[PDB]
Amino acid sequence: SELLVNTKSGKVMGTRVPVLSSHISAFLGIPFAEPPVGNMRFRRPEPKKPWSGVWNASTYPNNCQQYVDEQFPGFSGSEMWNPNREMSEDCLYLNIWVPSPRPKSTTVMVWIYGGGFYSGSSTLDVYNGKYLAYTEEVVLVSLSYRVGAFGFLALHGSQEAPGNVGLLDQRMALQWVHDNIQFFGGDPKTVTIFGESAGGASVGMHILSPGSRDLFRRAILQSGSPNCPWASVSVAEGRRRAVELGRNLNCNLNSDEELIHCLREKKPQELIDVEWNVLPFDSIFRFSFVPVIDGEFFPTSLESMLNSGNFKKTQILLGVNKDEGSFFLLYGAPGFSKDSESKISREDFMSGVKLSVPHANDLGLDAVTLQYTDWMDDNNGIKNRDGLDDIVGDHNVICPLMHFVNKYTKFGNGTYLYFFNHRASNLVWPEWMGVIHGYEIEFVFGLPLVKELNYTAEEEALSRRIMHYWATFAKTGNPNEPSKWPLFTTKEQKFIDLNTEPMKVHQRLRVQMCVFWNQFLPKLLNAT
Amino acid sequence: SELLVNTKSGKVMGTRVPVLSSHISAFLGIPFAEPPVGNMRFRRPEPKKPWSGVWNASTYPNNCQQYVDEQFPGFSGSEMWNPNREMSEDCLYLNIWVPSPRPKSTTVMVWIYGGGFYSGSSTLDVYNGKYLAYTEEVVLVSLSYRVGAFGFLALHGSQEAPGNVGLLDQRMALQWVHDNIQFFGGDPKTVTIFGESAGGASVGMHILSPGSRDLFRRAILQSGSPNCPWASVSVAEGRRRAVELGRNLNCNLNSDEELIHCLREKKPQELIDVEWNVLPFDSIFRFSFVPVIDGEFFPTSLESMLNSGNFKKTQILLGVNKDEGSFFLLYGAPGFSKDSESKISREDFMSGVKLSVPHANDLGLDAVTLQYTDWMDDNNGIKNRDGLDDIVGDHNVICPLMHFVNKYTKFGNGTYLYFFNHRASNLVWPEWMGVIHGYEIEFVFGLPLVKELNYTAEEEALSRRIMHYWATFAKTGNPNEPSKWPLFTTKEQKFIDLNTEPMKVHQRLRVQMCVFWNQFLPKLLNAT
Ligand SMILES: c1ccc2c(NCCCCCCCCNc3c4c(nc5ccccc35)CCCC4)ccnc2c1
Ligand SMILES: c1ccc2c(NCCCCCCCCNc3c4c(nc5ccccc35)CCCC4)ccnc2c1
Ligand SMILES: *[C@@H]1O[C@H](CO)[C@@H](O)[C@H](O)[C@H]1NC(C)=O
Ligand SMILES: *[C@@H]1O[C@H](CO)[C@@H](O)[C@H](O)[C@H]1NC(C)=O
Ligand SMILES: *[C@@H]1O[C@H](CO)[C@@H](O)[C@H](O)[C@H]1NC(C)=O
Ligand SMILES: *[C@@H]1O[C@H](CO)[C@@H](O)[C@H](O)[C@H]1NC(C)=O
C-alpha cells in the first residue's frame, strides 16, 4: 500500500488527502522523540523508542503547550496563528506530505514554525503542506518543538534544564528526516530547512551550530535571522529569568535542583500564566524564553561566529516583508488599534520608541527618534505611525537579517535575497498594517491556488512563482529555472521585489537605516 | 559748505564723490579712538581727543594689521577681501557716506565687517557705501576695529589685555555715531547696525551685551550669529592661546605683565607670523583670537543669556547663503582645489569631517558622517563634496543662526529671515562652491547697479530690492513697503528665498540638519 511505510522506528499508516481535485498521501503525527513529560520536562529530548505494529498517522498531533491569543476572539486574522489542536506537553511529532505516486528520491523541504519561541504549531491551516508537495513534487515535512519555558528555560550548568532544548527538539526531527525520509521517497542528501520569524532565526541557528550542520543541505530564512535582538539571551539573563519564573510560582530558590523540581510539579498553564512576568523591560518584540548562547549549541557569541566563518557553508535564500513591525505595535504600543487608522500623536510615538528599543539609554532613544522623525512635519499622525512601524521592523527583523546576509555571503556558496511587498487583496487586517509579519507564508504554501480563499488571478500567479522559486532552490541551490533573480554578492548586494508586478532588481536593501542599527547605535550604546 | 561738518570732536572736511552719474558727500577716515599703539596695544580703546582745525576726511584710512591672503595672487575672487590700504596699528577710523543735499534727520546704517575676527577692512570695494547711501537716502557708516591678537588677545584678570577690545572698538564707534551723526544729517535714534560673518556675530554680540544695547536701534545679521562655534572662547582657552602665542615668540612667561610686555615689543608682523600656531586643533573654520565670555562684555554664557531673554529686544533681519562652507574647504581640506570640480573621495570626506568638527570624539565623527552620507551611493564624488560643503555651512553658520533666531524671536519685537541662493552670473569662483560665504554682500551694497561690473538686468533688480528691503527695515523695523516678506514667528518660522525668481515663502530653514547640530550632537558629545 501507498499509505504504508516502514521506517527504522516502526511502520506508519498515512491517509490519502485531496488537493486541487487530485490527491496525495499524508503521514500526520509521526513521533520523533519520547514524550517530554514529568521528570523529562526541560530536559534534552530523547529519541522515540521503536514501536511494533502500525502507527496510525492519519490525523494531526497535539500542539505544544503555549499562551493563546484572545485579543480578537474569532477574528480569523489572529486565530489563524493559535493552536488548532488540543495542547499537550506530549507534542513532539512531525508531519509528512508525499506526492502520489510515492517518489523514489526527490527534493525534501522541512518547515520550522515561528511564534517568538513561545508559541506556534505545525498544524495551522496556513502551514498545510499539501499544495506545495503536490504542485512542486517535493516531500514536505513540518516538525514541531517545545516552546516557552518548556523549550527554553535555561539554568546553565544544570543538566536538568540546560536550555536550548527546543532547538534540540528541532535537531532530533532533522536527524529523523535524515535517517528515514528515503522510505517516503525523499532524498536525505537534498533537504532544505525553511522557516519564518523564530523559525527563520532557528534555521539560521542550525546553520551556525556545529551539531546541526550536517543534517541538512540548504536553507531558507523568512523574516528572521539568528542574530535577531529577540532571538537569544546570555546564560546569565536566561538564569535570571528562570529564577524570576520560579519566584512568580512561590518556588524554593535555594538551588537549581530545588527550582527545577518546583517548576516540574506545576501544571502547564501555571507556567504560561506568569511566563511574561520575567521580561527585564517594558518592551515590544521580546519574548521570555528563548535560545541561550551557552558555549555548546552555540560555541561562541553569534557575532564572532559570523565574523570568523564559523558556520555551514552552502546556499541560502531569504528575505523580509515591507511592514514587519506593524502587528507588534497593534498588540503592545499605545495609540494603535485594530479598527482605526492609528494615526499616532507625538507623545505616543515617543512612548512607542521607548518600548521598541527597551535596552536603550536616553541618548540612544534620542538617536532613534531623530533618525525616524520628519522635523518639518512632526505632528503628522500617519508619519508618526509609519515611522514607528519602520523602527520596529528595521530593528527587529530587517537590519539584523541584512547584517546576517552580508556576513554570510562573504563565506557562503550562494545567496538569494527578496523583499516581499504585496498586500493581499483579501487581507482581514486594516490597511495601516501594510505587508504584515507572517503574510508571505500563505503565498509560500500556495493558499492562493484555492478558489474559495478568494485571492486574485495575479495572486495565484505570484504564489505559483514563489512556490516554484522555493522548490527549485531547494532542489538545486538556485531559485532560477536554467526573468532572473540575481545572486546577492557582497559587491553588488542585489535583491528582488516579490509582488504581482514585473520583477524589479534593486540593491542595498535599507542600507541607510541599517548602517544606523547595525553600526552606529550599538557603538553609541556601548560608549554611553 | 556741504563738505564741512562740525562735530563734538572737531571739524571735518569731506569729499564729493560721483555715484551712478550723480554725486554725494563722503567723509572718509574720521578718527573715533586714540591710536592703539605702543603701551596702548591690547588695551581698551580710549576716545579720540578733540582736535582744533579741520580734519581732512577726503581719503580712506589705513586698514588694521592683519594676515594677508596670498593663495591666488591677483585673483580678484580672493584679493577683493585683502586690505587695499597700507596696514597700521593706527587704524581706528570710521567712514560716512551722506546723501546730497545733506539730510536733516534720516535713517542711519552702520556696517561692521567680517573676516573671522583676524582680518577685514572697512575700505574694500565691496563695502563702498555710496550706492546704498545714494539709492536709499540713508547715511551709511562703516566702522573699523582691531582684529587678530591686537583686538582679541585675552588674559582675563589683567587690565592690560582684558580681551574683547576689538568689540569695544566697535562700541566706541557706535558711541561716536550716537553722539555725532545728527551733524551729518543722520537720526541717532534710528541707527541699524549690520554686518556679515564675524560682523554679523559682532552685531549679535552688541544685541547681547548690556553695555552696547542702548547705542543702536535695530539689527541685521548676515551669515553670522553670536553663538557661532568659532565666534568666542572661554577665558581659560583665551588665556592658553595668549600664553602659547608668547611661547612662539620666546617670551618670558612667568606673569601676565611679563607676557604682555614681551608681546608689546614685537613688531606687528611677528605676531601675525605665528598667530595661527595657537589653535588647539587641526581644524577648519576656527580662528585664533576671538571674543571671550568674560563676565563683563558678556555677563554670563551666551546660551543662558539667550535662554533668559537677557538681551536687547527690538527687530532683527538676518539670514544665510546656500553654500556657506565651500570656501573654507577650498582653503583647508584635502581634495578641494580652485580649478577642478573637487569631486571628493571617501577618505578625503572622512578627513574633511575630522577638520570640520575639531572638538569631536569618534562617536561624534561617526554621527556626523552617518548624517551626511548617502549609503546607497557612498563613492559618489559630487555627493561627498556637497555633503562636506553642507556640514561646514550647517555647523558653522546656518544651524547656529537658526538656534539664535528661534531663541531671539521668543522675546524680540519682530524677525525677518532670508535664504540667499542666487549664484551671480559673473562669479569668478568655480561652480562647485555655489552661493559662497560673503557673496550676498555685493548685492546688499548694490554693485549690480554699475554696468561695468557686468551683472544681468535681473541681478540689478535683485540688488535694488535687497537694498530697499534693508533700508526700509532700517527705517521702520519692517522690510516691507506698507509681494510680502512675512514675519518669522516661533510658531510658523517662515522665511523667504532671496534670488531672481518670484519670491517664495518656506518654513523651518534646515530644521532636519539643525535638530542634529543643535540638540543631538551636543547632547552626544556631553555624555560620551
Ligand atoms: C500577559 C500579557 C501579554 C502576553 C503576551 N503578549 C504577546 C504580544 C506580542 C505577540 C502577539 C502576536 C500573536 C502571534 N501571532 C502572529 C504570528 C505572526 N504574524 C501575526 C500577524 C498578525 C497578528 C498575529 C500574528 C507570524 C508568525 C509568528 C506568529 C504573550 C504571552 N503571554 C502574555 C501574558
Ligand atoms: C598659517 C597658515 C594658515 C593661516 C590662515 N588661514 C586661514 C584660512 C581660512 C580663511 C581664508 C579665507 C580668506 C578670507 N576672505 C574671505 C572672506 C569672505 N568670503 C570669502 C570667499 C572666498 C574666498 C575668501 C573669502 C566673507 C567675509 C569675510 C572674509 C590665516 C591666518 N594665518 C595663517 C598662518
Ligand atoms: C486512526 O486514528 C484516528 C484517531 O481519531 C481514528 O479516527 C481512525 O479511525 C484511526 N484509524 C485506524 C485504522 O486505526
Ligand atoms: C559554489 O561552490 C562551487 C564549488 O566549490 C564553485 O564552483 C562555485 O563558484 C560556488 N558558487 C558561489 C555562488 O560561490
Ligand atoms: C587731504 O589729504 C590728502 C592726503 O593724501 C591730500 O591728497 C589732499 O590734497 C588733502 N587736502 C587738503 C585740503 O588738505
Ligand atoms: C512690537 O511691540 C509693539 C509695542 O510694544 C507691539 O504692539 C507689537 O505687536 C510688537 N510686534 C511684534 C512683531 O511683536
Image (cartoon, coloured by chain):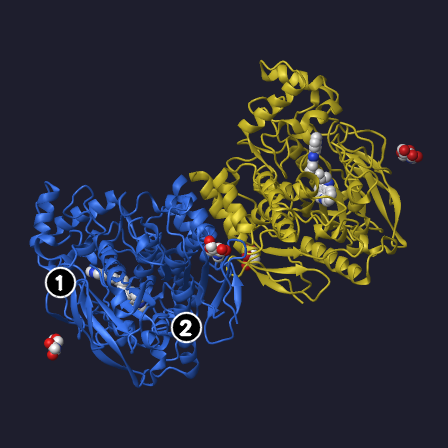
Chain colours: A yellow, B blue
| Quarter containing the N terminus of chain B | bottom left
The secondary structure type at the circle numbered 1 is loop
Q: Quadrant of residue B275?
A: bottom left
Residue type at the position of mark 1? Asp
| Mark 2 chain | B
Q: Badge 1: how crowded within 10 Å, few (<14), some, or many (20+)?
A: some
| Mark 1 chain | B
Image location (x, y in percent) of residue B464: 41, 76
Please report the residue visible at 64 percent of the width from the left and 58 percent of the height from the top: A478
In the image, the residue with mark 1 has its CB under 8 Å from the nearest atom of ligand 5: no
Q: Along the line of sight, which residue is nearer the eye, A427 or A162?
A: A427
Q: Along the line of sight, which residue is nearer the eye, A114 or B147?
A: B147
* Residue denoted by label 2: B468
Does label 1 lie on the same chain as label 2? Answer: yes
Image location (x, y in percent) of residue A444: 74, 52
| Quarter containing the C terminus of chain B | top left
On the question of residue A72 being in view, the answer is yes
Image location (x, y in percent) of residue A140: 76, 47
Between the C-alphas of marks 2 and 1, the distance is 35 Å
Q: What is the number of the mark on residue B90? A: 1
Q: Badge 2: how crowded within 10 Å, few (<14), some, or many (20+)?
A: some
Report whether A310 appears left or right of A466: left
Position of residue B241 relative to residue B77, above or below, is: above
Q: Give the farthest residue toward the left.
A: B265
- Which tag is nearer the camera, tag 2 or tag 1? 2
Report whether A257 appears left or right of A445: left
Report whether B54 appears left or right of B224: left
Please report the residue visible at 90 percent of the width from the left and 54 percent of the height from the top: A21
Image location (x, y in percent) of residue B347: 37, 59
On the question of residue A313 being in view, the answer is no
The secondary structure type at the circle numbered 2 is helix
